[PDB]
Image (cartoon, rainbow over all chains, first blue to last red; front, side, top):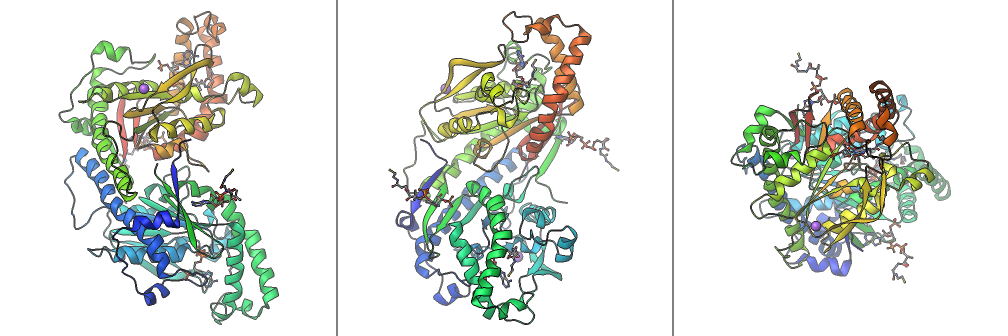
Length: 307
Length: 307
Ligand SMILES: CC(C)(COP(=O)(O)OP(=O)(O)OC[C@H]1O[C@@H](n2cnc3c(N)ncnc32)[C@H](O)[C@@H]1OP(=O)(O)O)[C@@H](O)C(=O)NCCC(=O)NCCS
Ligand SMILES: CC(C)(COP(=O)(O)OP(=O)(O)OC[C@H]1O[C@@H](n2cnc3c(N)ncnc32)[C@H](O)[C@@H]1OP(=O)(O)O)[C@@H](O)C(=O)NCCC(=O)NCCS
Ligand SMILES: CC(C)(COP(=O)(O)OP(=O)(O)OC[C@H]1O[C@@H](n2cnc3c(N)ncnc32)[C@H](O)[C@@H]1OP(=O)(O)O)[C@@H](O)C(=O)NCCC(=O)NCCS
Ligand SMILES: CC(C)(COP(=O)(O)OP(=O)(O)OC[C@H]1O[C@@H](n2cnc3c(N)ncnc32)[C@H](O)[C@@H]1OP(=O)(O)O)[C@@H](O)C(=O)NCCC(=O)NCCS
Ligand code: NA
Ligand code: NA
């Protein structure tokens, strides 16, 4: 029976690369790769290149839609030096690799013929300060939809897509586990804005950020595998992030493999998994493209929305 | 500050008519007008004509989007004798006039230069039979999201937009207040499908009909006004629909103005209003165009989504 989607295996998907040129060195790929990710240039070729193609094909097609409405309104026919920003959302669980996926996407798109302005913004910057979370009693729901200033987020994305000359966003520090006082990320009328976050594909009783997406990505994986990557990355951070005396979780550095496994599992069981199950996964059906990852972090299956 | 919308008054909106030709007689408008509606040809000119324009401008632009994806997929470049159906949703409360709006829209679009196949389908046909509603204990929630076979509905709309040669839908009888046994509406690869219903702009944890809309309309009005139209139409039906011995509500025919006002208010208070407040209104922010109606049923304000 009919379906809104169409599924590919890596073999079928890479065929769609065509003449798309690889403009990324191995050393650049490394500075984009997050702890735990196994992505190599081969994957950038067989998975991320066809994706970059499909996107530029549509950046063109999506512009005709705003054209048509501008014509209808009798408005001018706006500046080709400043078209309507193309918004891309990247969603998925904690520790599934969405940040790496989003950084890689930004790199490939910024290296297209013209050299379009491609900004990347994470929703982390819109989380409430820890003091405000404790106030709202949400310290153990950090990551959940309500742990974000969704109003400020929508204001930011709306501002940008509406053609503002510049829009600002707060900044989050993973090291201190909190928002940074006075820090800001300035986005200046980019050609493309990638919004990466747990909650980005979310819908609701009010117009939301996902309603402004022109394209969306959902980095997927078997839940038991994501837990493994989570715990695994947690033990690994004892000697990276947590090893920093300034780290909010510096106490975790001295944990034993066993103590660490227990702690990481409890956090996953009580916080990230519930959120993934109750809020993130339910948004997956709406993603334009779902990148399915095998236990080895490898992307071997994809689900595209044709409707 | 920036906004996803742009609001017009009738004066600003009619200006956008341009050369759009009125192809509707007064007698045809009458056979489209529902009991209680005050729509005249003037409104068809100053409100529905600009709308018909904006739509054909986009039917063209929306086709480029499926083109781009077909190109990406290396697929052919499908039959201009059978393009991807353009889906239009029409939502709003009970008794706000959405059915009239949808019939009028169908008429104007079917009378465009080529003479596109424009089918109209109401979600009434997807309600569960009364016996099944009583089973589910939903007889007093008739109209609510769960009172519909949403699975069958999504199957129907997906089938159609996916290019099926024909798709079938059940049929609902307002007279008998129930689904008609064995009746079916056949939709054969129309150029445009208008889906009219209370719940159509609804979102959820699964891909839904609203996710397949290429354009959407939300017929709006002050809630106290809609109640008035509801009660008002209820008294009026004592001598139209209810006057029919075959009518499920034939007992209502003998009610006095006073008895009738009480009954209609109770039904509105306990069923339609709650649904409007809890489920329909929350979908309004997502409609492409909101037609606001004054107490006299007149459309004097509009809200368009530019983003
Ligand atoms: C704060 C939070 C909502 C952020 O979610 P997120 O950024 O989507 O999580 P991700 O898995 O995508 O991680 C994003 C980046 O932050 C890094 N990171 C996560 N936690 C970190 C930490 N405590 N210190 C340093 N870096 C960290 C990830 O390694 C990743 O780095 P990369 O972009 O180079 O690959 C989430 O991490 C969180 O705290 N969730 C619930 C609370 C929790 O898990 N607490 C345990 C903390 S040890
Ligand atoms: C064990 C078994 C049933 C796999 O699970 P399933 O329940 O079949 O689901 P799938 O294999 O399609 O995929 C499993 C998960 O990966 C996802 N997935 C599969 N293909 C995907 C793709 N192309 N893109 C993204 N995600 C994909 C599924 O959506 C599901 O997601 P979730 O479990 O996180 O909700 C599998 O062994 C099987 O039988 N597959 C049917 C194939 C077949 O030959 N069938 C003949 C029947 S006679
Ligand atoms: C069944 C129901 C869900 C249908 O909703 P709906 O079709 O969106 O309601 P609308 O206000 O759009 O009415 C659509 C059409 O059906 C007509 N209609 C509504 N109820 C009718 C009835 N009992 N008998 C005959 N026609 C009726 C309306 O006049 C309108 O006609 P038109 O298209 O020519 O203008 C809704 O009417 C309902 O029953 N809601 C809750 C129960 C209720 O109100 N019961 C009181 C019945 S008197
Ligand atoms: C009484 C008063 C406040 C009206 O209500 P409001 O609370 O202002 O809301 P609006 O007048 O914009 O509209 C009222 C309703 O109609 C809707 N509406 C207004 N314009 C609309 C449009 N263009 N399209 C669709 N709907 C519209 C609103 O969304 C609202 O919907 P809802 O009540 O069903 O949720 C009005 O008298 C007023 O003060 N308007 C402000 C105009 C003005 O001159 N302000 C100067 C302030 S110093
Ligand atoms: Na910028
Ligand atoms: Na047909």
